[PDB]
Length: 105
Length: 118
Image (cartoon, chains in turn orange, yellow):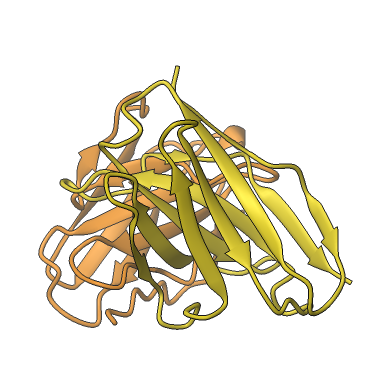
């Protein structure tokens, strides 16, 4: 398996602040990474696919970057509503895997 | 609109089994994989296995082989997941989720089915 690693389980930010959540692959997955948002009592929500591409309906203040092994998720202006856990996932090979998570404050 | 409506929550006894359903609507039920994902309380995302509605071909997370059985019914466009030999370690929140073949990702998720083995 490929190991998605979000070395930070938590990250504190404020409204209007910029925050970047990193994910690292145990091996080269190119752009084959996807990010999700799980709010309290809500289901996972695809925000990014293929490392950087935003899915349909996703706001503009969310962005992501990375290739190969080092990857990063970003929010330019955090909003109260952005309160959620965030997971990276590799979509490069079998089996599919997720990051540990980075519960955002 | 596309929707994945799962069966209701479950309170089960240890050693029993439970078959969790997932009704699909709004899209071609046979043009997408149907995966499942286990999340023990406050834990990370853990993929279980997919099934191909087109032929019922399944693939499992090697951890969950023997634990889960993935079945599907095209006529009702409902995918199921039956767990056997339950204990409290399996007491978790499970999500049925759709996946395109390419580009691969999880674009839709059910509301969630909360299992509690007691």
